[PDB]
Image (cartoon, rainbow, N blue to C red; front, side, top):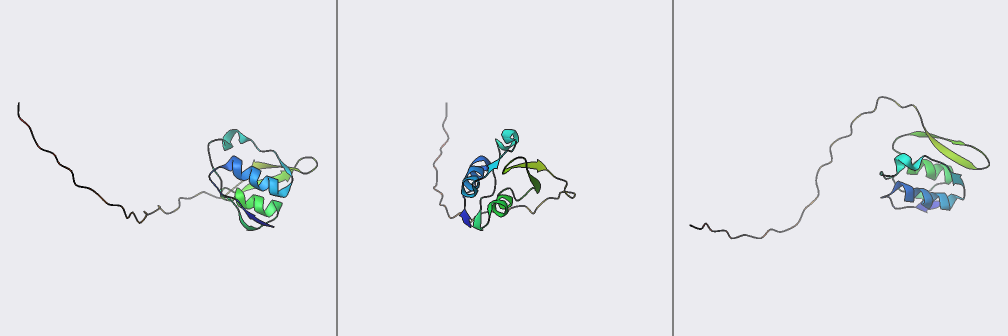
Amino acid sequence: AQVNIAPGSLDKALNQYAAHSGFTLSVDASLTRGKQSNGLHGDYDVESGLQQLLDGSGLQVKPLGNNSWTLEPAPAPKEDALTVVGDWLGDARENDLEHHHHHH
């Protein structure tokens, strides 16, 4: 199922995919409020697409009752540091300025 969601908000990206799937999800938004998540792009089911959204930290998803799933902290290897981002093209222009000294 082709699902394209724009990032810039974890809470949003959640409702976006959650609405496309049709299931319930219970996750501690306490920590969520303040961070963002990677949107989706391509044919991905409820689970496939869901894992693609939070994809980046690696967590576990398990159901609770009917069709309600939750996200919990799972074990991971010794985290590392990714390369440092470079810069953009920056094709702007600059204007000259005038300044003269004065006496008493």
